[PDB]
Amino acid sequence: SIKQLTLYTAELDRMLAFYTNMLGAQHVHEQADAFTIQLGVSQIQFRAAADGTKPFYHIAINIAANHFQEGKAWLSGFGELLTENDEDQAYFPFFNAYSCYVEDPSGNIIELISRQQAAPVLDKPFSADQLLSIGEINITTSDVEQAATRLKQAELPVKLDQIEPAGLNFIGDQDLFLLLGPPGRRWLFSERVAVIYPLQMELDNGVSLAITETGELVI
Ligand SMILES: Cn1ncnc2c(=O)n(C)c(=O)nc1-2
Ligand SMILES: [Mn+2]
Image (cartoon, rainbow, N blue to C red; front, side):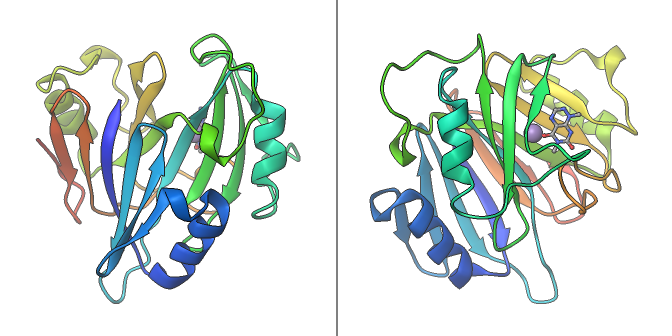
């Protein structure tokens, strides 16, 4: 799983307010020119973006198998649900998962994903305290093949011969997938096309990786 994720934002103030209101003060901590949010076992640190840039990403958050309708209702309280092909949710047969989406103040595409067999059934009400972990993050890179290769050299599940340098590649299994692909591809549920922005990531198993501002995945 993702222990720590570092992202950039050109809307630090609005983002801090947005997440404080969504998650509650007990999951959101203001720092110096940054703030953190805790999503179950995953933390995201949002740092101030460079001037002249407007970084955004696609982040999916795992929720329990039985929590989708409550999750969707909850998410809708924080912004208009995004739609694709006139639908305000998706079923993804490959993940056997239900998803819903909202845009945050930076234009991040924030998804709740409820994996129907790859997430637990929690017999309790859903709430902001029931977000389990980060289930997806985009790895938008200037070199998909290089990125896929290094991710394998990092001991992640990768089938190199299946990698599509011009398309989106699902890297992972169980409840975490890295969405590896090139810039230019429009994100489902969004008007925004994928753009390379820097980030850093620490997995629970100690592996550390980063995407530079020009799109190079490094370990
Ligand atoms: C292909 N695909 N499968 C599953 N989920 C997505 C998704 O959330 N987004 C945002 C996307 O652009 N493409 C997807
Ligand atoms: Mn997604």
